[PDB]
Image (tube, coloured by chain):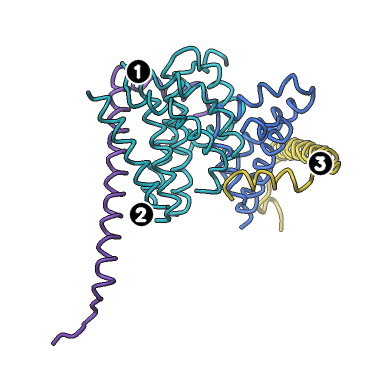
Chain colours: A yellow, B purple, C cyan, D blue
Amino acid sequence: SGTGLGEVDVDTYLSNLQTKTTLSMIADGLERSARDFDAFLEENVTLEWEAQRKRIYQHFGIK
Amino acid sequence: SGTGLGEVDVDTYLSNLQTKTTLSMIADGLERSARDFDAFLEENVTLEWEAQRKRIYQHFGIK
Amino acid sequence: DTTCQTAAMILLNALVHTSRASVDCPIIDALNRLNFIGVLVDSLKEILNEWASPSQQYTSAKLALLLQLCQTRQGAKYVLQANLFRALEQSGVFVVALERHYALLVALARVVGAAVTARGAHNIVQGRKFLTQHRGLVVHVLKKNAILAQQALEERIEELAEAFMLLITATGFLEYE
Amino acid sequence: VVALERHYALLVALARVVGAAVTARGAHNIVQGRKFLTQHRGLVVHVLKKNAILAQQALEERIEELAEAFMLLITATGFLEYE
């Protein structure tokens, strides 16, 4: 068989390839930014007062 | 019939009466406070700018 | 006592309410001389711990009273001097269970909203800090509004959303951008 | 459920920018942080109390980040001392 079976055309094939590459780039950038932010927060919070920062509020505010 | 059918005793009857009166008083006070606040807001907002106050935000903030 | 303090708190609401109908009032003035407004604003701290239940209904009358004093022009003077902005910050407060949660936020928002728009440009400086320091939270409420328990919950959102909106237009946060 | 998740994503982004800014310089920016929490009080209280299938976990995750975002500003700004 052949000549077309749930297939696409080259003009649309290249467009789909470019769209997929762009989406993958955006997703990778977002994931890297999120990971960098998480690492920064972990480095800044691991110094001290890990649970006290929330305990003070749980004691002040309504539990 | 008689001598008791899903009934209560006088010692509990008076307590239930007092509890009902207290609950009704609290509910009436809350409702009157809410009505007074609503009337005050209606009197203060009916002056002018009834829809503009929200339109400015809908235009500034994300709809 | 649990019932005496509740009835006494609600009683003061009727006194100040009926007195205004009779721009000043001698009842509100007496409360300031007796150091009642001072200790009252101090109790606002740790309100989360206090908040059908007897403690819940008691707090309702408490915040309800403060809301009335912020409606008269003279109340802004005595109320503002109590430094209520710093009292509500230490507490960290900022289907039926959720409805009660918004009921508390509305009560606090109304007291602050009416207070800023009471005196004039002397309190707008504080209102901007409250919205800027707690930005984002109000944005979620203003966008949410834009069976019995459901309607009751949504009703509080409408009141809560409209509460902050009054403070914005009254404080002039749009000019700050 | 997906629409709400995107809403919190915006609030988190803004909260992080403001949270990190106040705790960056020092006591010169704490005066502004207190006004932001006092002027927008109540809204943050709802988030800090909420945290205390795929789309559900994603939505709750943003609440945890959003709730912890303001908490960092509080301890860094010193709003507890103001009471």
Hey, which quadrant is residue C65 in on the image?
top left
10 Å neighbourhood of mark 1: few (<14), some, or many (≥20)?
few
Secondary-structure class at tag 1: loop
Q: Which residue is mark 2?
A: C147
* Apparent side of residue B22 relative to residue A29 in the rendered image (left or right): left
Image quadrant occupied by the C terminus of chain C: top right
Closest to the camera, between mark 2 and mark 3, is 3
Hey, which quadrant is residue D68 in on the image?
top right
Calculate the distance from the C-alpha at mark 1 to the C-alpha at mark 3.
47 Å
Residue C78 location (% of width, % of height): 45, 22
Hey, which quadrant is residue C86 in on the image?
top right
Secondary-structure class at tag 2: loop
* Apparent side of residue C67 relative to residue D1 in the rendered image (left or right): left
Calculate the distance from the C-alpha at mark 1 to the C-alpha at mark 2.
33 Å
Q: Which residue is mark 3?
A: A45
Q: Amino acid at mark 1?
A: Trp
Residue C92 location (% of width, % of height): 60, 39
* Apparent side of residue C168 relative to residue D80 in the rendered image (left or right): left
Residue drawn 23% across and 77% down?
B7
Q: Chain of mark 3?
A: A
Residue drawn 55% across and 30% down?
D40
Q: Amino acid at mark 2?
A: Ile
Q: Chain of mark 2?
A: C
- Quick check: C26 above or below A18? above
| Callout 1–callout 2 Cβ contact below 8 Å | no
Q: Which residue is mark 1?
A: B49
